[PDB]
Image (cartoon, coloured by chain):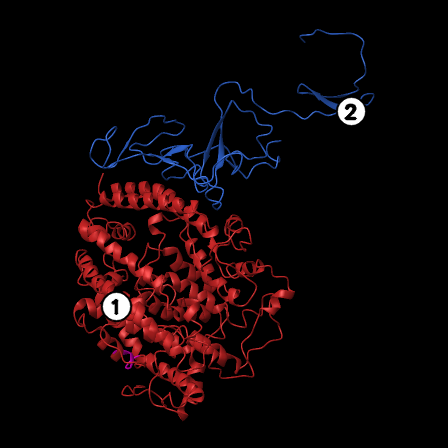
Chain colours: A red, B blue
Amino acid sequence: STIEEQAKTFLDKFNHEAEDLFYQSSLASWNYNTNITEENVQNMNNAGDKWSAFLKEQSTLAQMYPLQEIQNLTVKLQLQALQQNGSSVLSEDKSKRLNTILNTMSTIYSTGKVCCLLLEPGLNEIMANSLDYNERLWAWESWRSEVGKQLRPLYEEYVVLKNEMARANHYEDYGDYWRGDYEVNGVDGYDYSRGQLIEDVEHTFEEIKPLYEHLHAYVRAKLMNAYPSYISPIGCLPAHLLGDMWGRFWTNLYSLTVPFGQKPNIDVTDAMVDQAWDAQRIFKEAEKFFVSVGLPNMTQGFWENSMLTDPGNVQKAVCHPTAWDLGKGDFRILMCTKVTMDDFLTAHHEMGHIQYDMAYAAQPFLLRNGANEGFHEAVGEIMSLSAATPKHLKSIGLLSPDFQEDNETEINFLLKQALTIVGTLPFTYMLEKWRWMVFKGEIPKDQWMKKWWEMKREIVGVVEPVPHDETYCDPASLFHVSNDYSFIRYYTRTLYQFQFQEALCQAAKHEGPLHKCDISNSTEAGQKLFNMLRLGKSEPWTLALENVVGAKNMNVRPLLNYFEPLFTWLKDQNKNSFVGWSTDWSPY
Amino acid sequence: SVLYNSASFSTFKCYGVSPTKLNDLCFTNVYADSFVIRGDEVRQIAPGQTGKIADYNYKLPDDFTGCVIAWNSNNLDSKVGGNYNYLYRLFRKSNLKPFERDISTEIYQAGSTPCNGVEGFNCYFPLQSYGFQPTNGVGYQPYRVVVLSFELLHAPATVCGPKKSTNLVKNKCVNFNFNGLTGTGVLTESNKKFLPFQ
């Protein structure tokens, strides 16, 4: 026997044993997520202990296999994600010390009380619905003086420990670990080194600034009615006037900014009460969306094992919107589905991930994963975007076939989407580039506050509402930082949302703007969609993008076509105030 | 004929011999290979396939003159949370001829190191466990496949088919056929007797 022939024996040996252990790890955790019981806590720890020990002992037997003699454009990609060094490459002393920091930063963030008052929905309502300048300021200033102080010493050690871990896996700094997933090396023609990922984003960000300047000027000129003195017509915006605690989610600002009071958005909540919708017809109408397009249908066990109802009074638990994948043909969804419009738009988000896992059903367990971390959520965004067009809701049961698309109605529809998709784009791009310079050496350890505040005025446009010092720490109180996660997956999610939508809407005779498109009864747009979903981890992300769009690089052009009517209305409205912001202005 | 329209089987494919011609056809020896496999392994049971199940476990010839009976249970059998009752061979260092059973619990040798007894590296366990769970989809359900073997040798075939009998009309000059003797006459009653062995 040779090398590639004996390598296939270890794959089938591991796949026939990992799927049995991974199914017990997800089944034990599913019982705790559907019924609060102390007995289910021990079953999750016992199932996770055997899974964590079996994965580490099988990776050692694959270390002696050469990583350069297997050529098949499929098996080579499986060994790169299995023969990795991982967090156990360091010594036994620094291994247990690094895991302790990850548990302390998550405890303070989850128990951060302001005396008591919790974060959400505790301080979330104060930072949104308040209509005052001296009321919502105390909720933001006290959060940095209590949570930022307890996370400052735990964040300094997080930089030095994670930097040495990345250098042991043949890299430069810690920033290369998050970018190593997009890096492709070993195939033929589909190569993509790290020298190109650094320039793909910095170029498209220069063209989105004119779109952000018109959106930021509309929020600044709107708050001048409530308080003219506190808001400068040419200045920036304080950090306590963005809705979110960290200034990332601008969805709460939609309640204070309303362009049209005559033609508001559509509401399909009352239309489902008369048509008998007992939280079951939502999934039935959503099933047809994945049938007449060219995608596989559902299964019989999907409607009998996935808890999609209410726990009632005898049982109670949680239901965070997150898709599950138990494996071996078992797929369940844990979402409390009610009878309103909020649950109708979010039903198609996790539903797109179900068709993703069903694409690579005949593939081994080592290929049941996306090409990158920024592609899993990209499948759920293109399904929820088409599920919000009034034309899509007209051909189904709910809504009235007498409603037509109005020019003034689309103005309010693009405003709420610009405060979430591109609303967090400048904040994500700034926070991602700021952390990449800490591990390198461009930002000193004692110059975090001096660098973080001077970059917000030049990109986001947020000054200092209250003078601080070099002791506070703002980025350490983030859900994706205190729990060890990457923020680069959200930046590419907003760009890949419009790239995959323009390709499907082009074959469906829906050119021009993307807000009037409707993916329904289109067999051609469904064939190209299943190609990149079936590939999974078998092929790099460069091939998955060409099969739908046609290229291998990101582009901001499809992002501007969806906001074309919004960019024109903001230009003729913000011309009376000021287009831009002055970084030399300070409220104090 | 009664085993085709019984409405108790999922799939019923016949190769070579038609499913509507074996009712009155004689067969020498009739065999039945009853076994249970997975859902994706049902398509592999065909004269002319290959893989890891139809090559090392149950080998099928190039030509097949019979039917393939397979239904679904997924109840009265199987378990929740995994199946730990039956096993199946995955890899094997040597091939097997068609119509041959392998009951040797040997160890597959992937590398060049001698296995059979000692494991650890390049010596994996070939017998794998199933996954019959009623909470999965369709391709993960147990299907009991009963392969029928229809052979025709020089031995006198004693397995044919029941002939359909009719009524008995008398006092009429009609046609009859008794023991392959085609005749046309009147079947009138008789009082004399013949011999019991004739």
Q: Position of residue A326 (x, y in %)?
A: 42, 49
Amino acid on which the number 1 mark rests in the picture: Leu
Secondary structure at numbered mark 1: helix
Asked whether the viewer can see residue A369, the reply is yes
Residue A161: image quadrant is bottom left
Look at mark 1 in the image and give the residue it sits on: A197
Give the Cα separation between the discs numbered 2 and 1.
95 Å
User: Which quarter shows the N terminus of chain A?
Assistant: top left
Image point (62%, 72%), residue name: A401
B51 lies left or right of B170: left
Instruction: Say if B27 sits above or below A446 in the image.
Output: above
| Classed neighbour count for the residue bearing mark 1: other residues with Cα under 10 Å, few (<14), some (14–19), many (≥20) | some
Q: Residue furthest bottom?
A: A576
Amino acid on which the number 2 mark rests in the picture: Val
Q: Position of residue A539 (x, y in %)?
A: 32, 56
A173 lies left or right of A420: left
Residue A18: image quadrant is top left
A150 lies left or right of B183: left
Pick whichever, A397 or A30, lies toward us.
Answer: A30
Asked whether the viewer can see residue A328, the reply is no
Region rendered in magenta: A455-459
Image point (16%, 69%), residue name: A441
